[PDB]
Image (cartoon, rainbow over all chains, first blue to last red; front, top):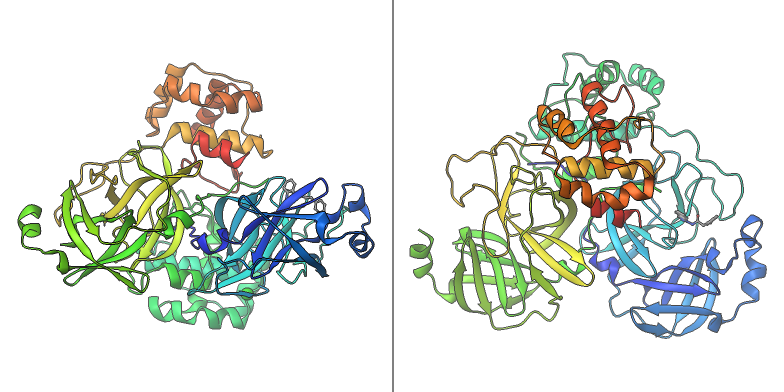
Length: 305
Length: 292
Ligand SMILES: O=C(Cc1cccc(Cl)c1)Nn1nnc2ccccc21
Ligand SMILES: [Cl-]
């Protein structure tokens, strides 16, 4: 019993964190096999950030300009290449702690663990979700660039995010491990703002199924809804549209608890209309949207209370 | 910017998790040097233990079987002497924590870590964790510098879904016993010094709608706080909040007057750090560490 925001054990990622220094800038890098991955803005000054020409800044650099530190050992850089907004530093030593891994690009609504680092040293781990506006509500300070997001389903680490910047609202933007940004963001200091954010509907529904699994049914009602009528109501509360794919994905939780997806949708419509009336759901007074249908199945029991 | 419930990196603890099997029971053990620590309920405990031999205990570290060469009991923890020292043993200490203190939990099943979360020792000595059958033996810890301080070992779940366990020396937190009997969590209270620390964190992150021009005495605040099932705030708590008070410019009793108004009037449709409830699972030190 219980339902916590749970992160994956970070050990497999801790053994990959390194410190990358270029001139006066110091940030984090991910050391996998003989390559160190880090944000390409490590080669920039604060002035350069307005309109940086990365190809022009990189051509002026040599291997020995990049200092890479793994614990108390200095790694030797033997090559460098750029792939989109990521810099790949070829090093002379393969990381003996390299876990089994894959680079995966995620979609909005997906969750992942973040290992926040400073100076190549891990300081904390937390769970978060890729928002519909492609930002993440993380907890990062100056020096955290290069920190990574990941999932560890089974024994394989799937790297899905690398931290690049903080937007003016305090939210964070970054790339996949191939250097492609999530969202319409660029690694440039220019007027950039996160689009209006929305609630991840399929995740709120999954969390309502988790509450039913843990023994709570106070929010259920005798009504059902059509998918279209649900979406017309949901869009008035800034909720993401619920698609047929989302309904299909909620199938297993619907079969486990005995509550059809559109009946759970009707309970959601009512909660949006009435609020909680002094009650909580899984210790929360707000509707939680940072647990996916897959997270609920992984964390909750297979036997409904 | 941002404020998340953050756990310590779990790697130093992952390298200590093992699977312990005795008969039909399978739970988790903590392998430090040549000793495996696990709940004694894996087996009148002296009478049950005397009937066991070393080979009855099966210990598995990854895909390798460890050889048990000795066994002893310390309070509600069983210590299994093994033939191999854990080469991954970190620098460590066994520490007993107080209610209100927070720690990270590495939840495990079959000696395999599955998740890490942050939680607090409630004033009623229970923890609001997330555990399933097979999680027994999972541990709670903090990291201070490069040293792991082990503070909790999971033993059981109470009928309300909350959890109970011991320190690493086998002494229970709370008036609980390790057996199937009628046990219940006492009435819980809110950790006041932690709510205040979380209000300072909100001010640091630019959330100031709850600030007011008022102050209060420590006694008047405590008369108010006890009415809402909040733990009493002591002069030690006020002293501990000193650095956050100097950083934000809001005196502790000034922040108490904000807390008094939040308890009597509610939040009025507003949130604080994305929460509609007053959060009490961040200590003053957690706030300073996450905001530095
Ligand atoms: O934002 C930057 C530098 C930067 C500026 C402009 C563009 C780019 Cl790609 C990078 N660093 N970061 N990242 N997270 C932070 C949290 C707080 C303070 C600074 C932080
Ligand atoms: Cl995805």
